[PDB]
Amino acid sequence: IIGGEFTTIENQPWFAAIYRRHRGGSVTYVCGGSLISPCWVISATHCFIDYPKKEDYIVYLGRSRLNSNTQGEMKFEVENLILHKDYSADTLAHHNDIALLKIRSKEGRCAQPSRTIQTIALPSMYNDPQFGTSCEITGFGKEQSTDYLYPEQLKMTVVKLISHRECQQPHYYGSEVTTKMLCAADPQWKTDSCQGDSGGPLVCSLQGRMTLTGIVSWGRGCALKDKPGVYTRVSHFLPWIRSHTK
Ligand SMILES: NC(N)=NC(=O)c1nc(Cl)c(N2CCCCCC2)nc1N
Image (cartoon, rainbow, N blue to C red):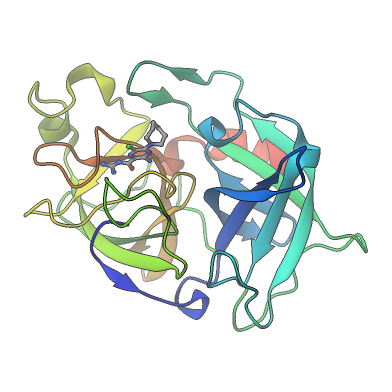
């Protein structure tokens, strides 16, 4: 997250932190995700496509810091890793960039909701907030494009939804943005998602309900003028989500 504010997991208690264990034994951060039911975290396929073995992954819930434990956190193995079969990637765009992780603890339990661990509601089909609506994004991604390190502390910021018309202009992304994607950005381009925020939640208030409107997917650089963040449009994937979680 470029700009924004530090936060703790109580403010985004559906946020999932996904790590990978290497053959060398070291564990590194991969991507964010969101808890949508006790046994299911939703994320982005591009996060796992290179290393699609479920066994290598670890998922934390209720975690506010990257490399230290947070009181109350839960740790899970990945029982199922479900990538979207129509995934594809260009040199920038990721299409159908959506994945599901079924989580299971070493005792064989799913998540237990708490003050730091809660599910996020899915949107109604094809039901998105109007352009110009303010939504929240959350992650452990870079604070500056030129940073080597990720922040130790969780961050969040606010971005406004951009119309498909505006995002499809040639100076923005042209055809790279599709109707299965949403764009969002700051009017001054001063705050944004970045590398390491992929898979994390774009949350909007819809009806009167915090709702998972998007999943961080891609962008050309971060917080660059005329280059919004691009998000998988969750309201266009409900049958896929339901089919793979039921
Ligand atoms: N919102 C904006 N502007 N960007 C992003 O969200 C974003 N930006 C980048 Cl550079 C990124 N990378 C960079 C390497 C290629 C893809 C994987 C990780 N992932 C993102 N999700």
